[PDB]
Image (tube, coloured by chain):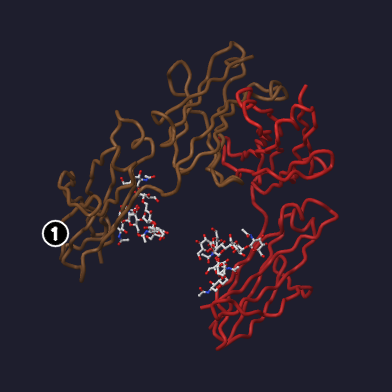
Chain colours: A red, B brown
Amino acid sequence: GPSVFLFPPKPKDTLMISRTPEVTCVVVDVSHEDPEVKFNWYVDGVEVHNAKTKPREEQYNSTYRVVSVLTVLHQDWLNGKEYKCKVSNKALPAPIEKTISKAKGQPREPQVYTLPPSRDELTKNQVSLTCLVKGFYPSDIAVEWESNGQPENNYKTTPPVLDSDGSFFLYSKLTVDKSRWQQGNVFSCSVMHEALHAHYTQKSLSLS
Amino acid sequence: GPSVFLFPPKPKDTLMISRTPEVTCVVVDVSHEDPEVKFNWYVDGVEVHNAKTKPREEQYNSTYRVVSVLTVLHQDWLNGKEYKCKVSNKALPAPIEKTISKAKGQPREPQVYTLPPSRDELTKNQVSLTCLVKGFYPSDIAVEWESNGQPENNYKTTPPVLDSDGSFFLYSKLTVDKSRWQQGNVFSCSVMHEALHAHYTQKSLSLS
Ligand SMILES: *[C@@H]1O[C@H](CO[C@@H]2O[C@@H](C)[C@@H](O)[C@@H](O)[C@@H]2O)[C@@H](O[C@@H]2O[C@H](CO)[C@@H](O[C@@H]3O[C@H](CO[C@H]4O[C@H](CO)[C@@H](O)[C@H](O)[C@@H]4O[C@@H]4O[C@H](CO)[C@@H](O)[C@H](O)[C@H]4NC(C)=O)[C@@H](O)[C@H](O[C@H]4O[C@H](CO)[C@@H](O)[C@H](O)[C@@H]4O[C@@H]4O[C@H](CO)[C@@H](O)[C@H](O)[C@H]4NC(C)=O)[C@@H]3O)[C@H](O)[C@H]2NC(C)=O)[C@H](O)[C@H]1NC(C)=O
Ligand SMILES: *[C@@H]1O[C@H](CO[C@@H]2O[C@@H](C)[C@@H](O)[C@@H](O)[C@@H]2O)[C@@H](O[C@@H]2O[C@H](CO)[C@@H](O[C@@H]3O[C@H](CO[C@H]4O[C@H](CO)[C@@H](O)[C@H](O)[C@@H]4O[C@@H]4O[C@H](CO)[C@@H](O)[C@H](O)[C@H]4NC(C)=O)[C@@H](O)[C@H](O[C@H]4O[C@H](CO)[C@@H](O)[C@H](O)[C@@H]4O[C@@H]4O[C@H](CO)[C@@H](O)[C@H](O)[C@H]4NC(C)=O)[C@@H]3O)[C@H](O)[C@H]2NC(C)=O)[C@H](O)[C@H]1NC(C)=O
């Protein structure tokens, strides 16, 4: 019947002390027949009571969806604590358990390189600015572009890819009008990751 | 009872005339009580009988696994014809129908750009050669590297990523010994895609 999906905090939230990371427990296919759901949360086995469950709400299919959110401490998530969400419902003979933690494995520092557009690309009115981020472990990561403190609209980032040494890599393509590039504007790829010092680094790229 | 799996040809196979693309119809779980299986092939609903089907091989889970291979015409697959493999078994109330055809959508031509390693990366013994392939549709594509006409296989390629204008892009990373890069060896990124002229193009990258 009702299924449960447990989601981790956003990388950004866990890596910036100013932000609040939370684990999210989503119960779907809750039926009108038995629409009561109780959540029990556990951090490394020990129960906790600061979860806020949202009021259940109807779906376009006539099931109910119901979500419980548990704020987590940056250090706890980064230190590898296990978060367990226990879901009990009258239609469930025995509760459903999902437990989640950060990716296991030795953390590896990302190397961040910026690559300008190929010469060939200057025959267009738009050009490709490239951020190559490689050698990192946990795949969990945030990569963003900006120019003079302002975030850039047109960019897309590949999913992380398992490289041969077992680290991950990825690329982010930033698209700007050629004039912006030829004007000598400075663009910046920002990267946030746990094995980075102060969880953050940025590399610049402009026309020299 | 018996299950049927229909497999598309490899992009690279459909794309190079000197290669042989084929659609593969795998039937698993055929009982020893109802072993006789017959294949009927239909291109755009028109039956064909040039399928080489291998004699049934016995597994370890008591069932057999028969394979039928249809060598398809390059042009055919690429013109979007529909390959219907119809397997008959006596343990079936009705003969299963599995059909397949190449992805639909307006074909778009990939732009291919080679990008040398950031200067920052020359502090390493290994460097990263980057191929940017963008603006293609069908996300079906083959990307490969070589040097001196010989394949260079220490590379990893990202999945196609849906870009903001509806087409796909990707990146291929080729890792070589810095010493090879600085002796000025020429590496080449070969792309194969249906929307390319002659279904092939290549860009080279060497020390500048
Ligand atoms: C009635 O409707 C509801 C609402 O659904 C909505 O219906 C209409 C309107 C359509 O628009 C739907 O697309 C729309 O969602 C239905 O509820 C849905 O139920 C399905 C399953 O039936 C769920 O699918 C799961 O999706 C998760 C990931 O979901 C995230 O991303 C989705 C899109 O990518 C997004 O839609 C979700 O909102 C969710 O988004 C995340 O949410 C959190 C919290 O807000 C947020 O922090 C994130 O930022 C956000 N992220 C993203 C990407 O947006 C997917 O992971 C599930 O896959 C698991 O299960 C599969 C088998 O069941 C299996 O193939 C996968 O491998 C995986 O299995 C797990 O695997 C791991 C390891 O691999 C293992 O450890 C686990 O044990 C294992 N779990 C198993 C096997 O159970 C899965 O595909 C939808 O999320 C859900 N939609 C919503 C919005 O709630 C409902 O089904 C409908 N009722 C009926 C009967 O049809
Ligand atoms: C008895 O044994 C046989 C085989 O023996 C085997 O060997 C023993 C010793 C064990 O080690 C076992 O490995 C195994 O028992 C069993 O037969 C198997 O049956 C399973 C299903 O139970 C099949 O799984 C399917 O796999 C396909 C993809 O298959 C390719 O990749 C596999 C790895 O993923 C690989 O193992 C296969 O060999 C195969 O390899 C490809 O072969 C082609 C042929 O030329 C070649 O071109 C390719 O290059 C090559 N690829 C490689 C090597 O990379 C997978 O696609 C199927 O997934 C679909 O179906 C699933 C349900 O089964 C479903 O969960 C998925 O979502 C997916 O569903 C699809 O959904 C979409 C959307 O609707 C739709 O487009 C699809 O049509 C739909 N498919 C549906 C609905 O059918 C699937 O998982 C195995 O291939 C098969 N093994 C072999 C080798 O034939 C048998 O089950 C055993 N009987 C028992 C248990 O009693």
For image coordinates 66% across by 46% down, the residue present is A138
Give whichever of A173, B130 is nearer the camera: A173
Q: Position of residue B60 (x, y in %)?
A: 27, 55
In the depicted structure, whether residue A188 falls above or below residue B105: above
Q: Position of residue A21 (x, y in %)?
A: 76, 60
Cβ at disc 1 under 8 Å from ligand 2: no
Q: State left or right for residue B121 relative to residue A187.
A: left
x, y percent for residue A195: 74, 42
Q: Kindly identify the residue that appears in the image at 60 percent across and 71 percent down.
A: A97
Viewer-proximal residue among A93 and B46: B46
Q: Point out the image quarter for the N terminus of chain B.
A: bottom left
| Image quarter hosting the C terminus of chain B | top right
Task: Please tell me which residue lies in front, A102 or B44.
Answer: B44
Q: Secondary structure at mark 1?
A: loop
Where, by quadrant of the figure, is residue A199 drawn?
top right
Q: Position of residue B107 (x, y in %)?
A: 45, 42
Residue named by callout 1:
B36
Q: Is residue B33 above or below residue A33?
A: above
Residue B29 picture quarter: bottom left
Residue found 25% across the figure and 52% down from its top: B44
| Three-letter amino acid code of the residue under disc 1 | Glu
Which of B97/B164 is in front? Answer: B164
Looking at this view, name the residue that lies furthest to the top: B183
The chain letter under disc 1 is B
At label 1, counting other C-alpha atoms closer than 10 Å, the crowd grade (few under 14, some 14-19, many 20 or more) is some
User: Would residue A50 appear left or right of B38 to someone viewing this image?
Assistant: right
Taking the image in four quarters, ligand 1 sits in the one at bottom right
Residue most extreme to the bottom: A33
B28 is higher (above) or lower (below) than B194: below
Residue at figure coordinates x 17%, y 48% from the top left:
B48
Q: Quadrant of residue A43?
A: bottom right
